[PDB]
Image (cartoon, rainbow, N blue to C red; front, side):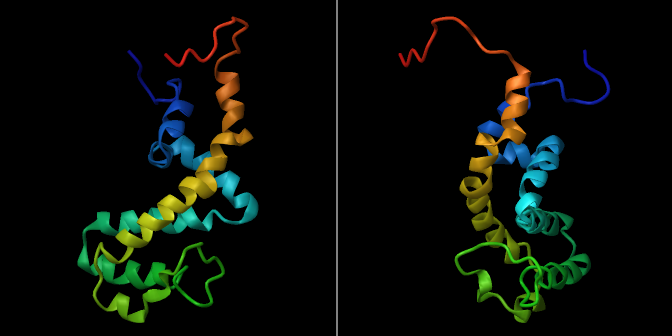
Length: 149
């Protein structure tokens, strides 16, 4: 019987399992960001998150705006923060013409994999995460090793 807010539950495990678990969770995003912000790369999660929210709204009017808004954010030339990708420049002011949850849906897919091995990968082997993973549970002094069968 736990009332109030979740947290005591093993979080690291979730984030470690799949990046999604970290993004969906508030704690994960809070930390993950800090790690990125360091090299001023967080902009990646800032654009990725939007992608979803956009399709979520499920509104034409609202979309009409958010569309160009986000586009003029990172999908712009004078974009102070341009995410890392292979070539998502294929889009253009036109992509804004008809707003749809498919314009970003894809752009978000690639970015996901990028951080999955770009940032995520590190996040795990990073102190920001480890620290918690350690303080969470002490080490074992038993001869018990990787059975592997």
